[PDB]
Image (cartoon, coloured by chain):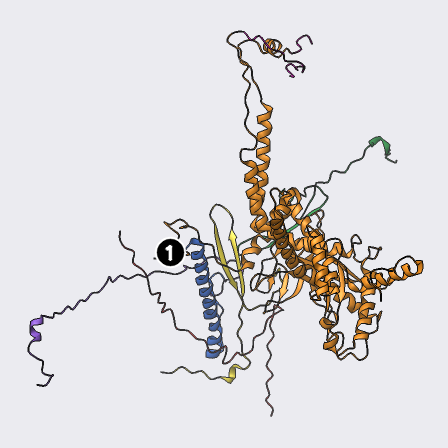
Chain colours: A yellow, B green, C purple, D blue, E orange, F red
Amino acid sequence: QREGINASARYPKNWVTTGDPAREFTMIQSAPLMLLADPDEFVSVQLA
Amino acid sequence: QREGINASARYPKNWVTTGDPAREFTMIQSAPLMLLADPDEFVSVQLA
Amino acid sequence: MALYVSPIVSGEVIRSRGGSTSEFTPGYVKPKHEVNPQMTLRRLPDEDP
Amino acid sequence: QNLADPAYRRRRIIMQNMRDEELAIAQVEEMQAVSAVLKGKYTMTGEAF
Amino acid sequence: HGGGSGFGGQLRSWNPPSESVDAALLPNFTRGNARADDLVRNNGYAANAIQLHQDHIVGSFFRLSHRPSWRYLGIGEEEARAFSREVEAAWKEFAEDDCCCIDVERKRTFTMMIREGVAMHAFNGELFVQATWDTSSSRLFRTQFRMVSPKRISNPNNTGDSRNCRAGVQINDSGAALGYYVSEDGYPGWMPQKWTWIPRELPGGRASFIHVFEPVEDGQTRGANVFYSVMEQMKMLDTLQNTQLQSAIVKAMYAATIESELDTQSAMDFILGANSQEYAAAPVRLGGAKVPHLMPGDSLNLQTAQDTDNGYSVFEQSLLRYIAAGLGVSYEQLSRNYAQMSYSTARASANESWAYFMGRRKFVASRQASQMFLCWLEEAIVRRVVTLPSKARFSFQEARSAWGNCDWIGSGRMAIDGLKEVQEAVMLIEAGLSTYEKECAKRGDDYQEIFAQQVRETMERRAAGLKPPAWAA
Amino acid sequence: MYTTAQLLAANEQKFKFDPLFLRLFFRESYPFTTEKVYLSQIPGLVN
């Protein structure tokens, strides 16, 4: 949010923790909400 | 201390903590010690 | 996957990668032969008379 | 025969990590699509969520 | 074979982490600038190098000479030169203005603009200038210029850099910058730092903000000062000279010593005379020889100290030679030492340094002044202070570069002998292989006003009726 | 320990995966600004 990218597909992020043990990270964040207009448009049937 | 500006009125600082709950914190530090040269110059009376 | 972690409780990470080896040292072949100049006297099937 | 410096190793590890992370996010996002056009119902359910 | 490992391992543990120059520079970009500022403020050598830059890249004056692309625009010579002289007269009136109102800071002239720009390009790697347009109508021209230190350009809230956001430089996919972020004054650091975004170019086509530096590879965004290759060397050199000075101080401080079992006061008054008759121990008056009479078992061991320049001078010679190599300036110019110098060697050194400085001038000051003149001329045209010829095939906005074709005249080449250069120049002119314009540009003038001044001179001499000058018939 | 053992191959053989649905059915992407999403359907049925 610090850079006004509130809406985005994928957000990379990296940071290294302090302290005696050193270790950094790679972060990806997203909130996908794949939807569709008409569910009745498609017909899905299991077979046997 | 490392910025060498340790002498003024109001010090602002906003910083972000690391890790997943990465959150910002805003800060206004000060050490105000205002004073008057002559206390006896000003005369106070408790009206009754 | 990292399926649906709520954005407060990120939690754990996953192992990076890695691991495999193999060793097969040289192979080798050396099919020698010979000359023996004595056989050179009688002619071969070719080399018509 | 030719080793690599620790910094180069860590850069390569970062490459592997970011690639697997994007693969995982693609894998998780296609789940919405397959649930949608398989039954129209979808359950965004996961531990710690 | 050379780049693999090194002979017998040798550089068996060294392998630089190959990356772009921006990736190498940005993480410690602030640190390098801080170290460079500290060096230029506390070290005499850095200050002298910067002063040489200021004196030689631009020097005392910086003249304009606008030669428009009249042939490209299909313009006639007469109106082309009329327009040129009018615009240059306007520019010279506006530039050396005694108001000192050219800038918002109101505390420098245009020559100081050029000097500050080249100096900050040298010791910071680049220069930033914002052209503002004030609303006050008190003066003819409403354009002012503000130079900004690179320390004031950074991403908002000191955020992490990205593909299209590097050090607060908004760029496109191709790498061309489109916007900048500027932080206001931070004195004291007790006001909340704020970021303002300024587009590089005004949508109307005006260069609202100009950023000048010399990239060395693809993808460059910021410049690197010349000190990066010599900063640690010069810092440690200053430390070494300081420590050597202090060591010599203490060596000269302790000269002799006395050895005796007796009381200290008695030893003083018996060996050094002292003033026992009157924790300062005992001061000693300075007089004649004062030969003592130390009793047996005593000693007056006078130390021989140690030479204060045990190769120090020549070691400094070599180190300053390396520093000059790094900084581009010649060693004699940098170190102000000129021993055992021959005419040919001095001429060669001057030629090399002058070529380098001409390159630096052309690649910093010429273009910065050209951009400033372009903005000023855009304002002048939009205010119609001069009349553009109607026959002009292309509009001003269409042919901005063509209309703004102008060169610059800096400080001339002051030859060591002078007589030789003047005689060679005049014989070259006689041979006709050069031009008065080229000669005056080299020497720091222009043939047009030279001829005007000569016409004035001959008119005055004719009126006085004393002697015609050396240009008649 | 004369085991220099130079290496030549780094085969992956990782995984088989291609969505084809997002490019076959969801060809349009949409960022969100609000927290809530409204999706409406109008039914047309008349006697």
**Picture quarter with the C terminus of chain E:** bottom right
* Quadrant assignment for the N terminus of chain E: bottom left
Q: Is residue F22 magenta?
A: no
Please determine whether, in this image, residue E141 is positioned above or below residue B24: below
Residue displayed at 63% across by 57% down: E355
Q: Residues within 10 Å of mark 1 (few under 14, many from 20)?
A: few
Q: Secondary structure at mark 1?
A: loop
Chain bearing tag 1 is D
Occupied quadrant, residue C17 = bottom left
- Residue B27, position as x, y percentages in the image: 66, 49
What amino acid does circle 1 point to? Leu
Which SS does the magenta portion mostly show? loop
Report if residue E148 is visible in the image: no
Q: Residue at point 61% right, 65% down? A: A5
Residue stretch rendered in magenta on the structure: E274-295
Q: Residue D11 appears at what percent x and percent y? A: 46, 58
E289 falls in the magenta region: yes
The one of E454 and D49 positioned closer to us in this rendering: E454
Height in image: E117 above or below E302?
A: below
Side of F1 relative to E460 (left or right): left
Tag 1 residue: D3
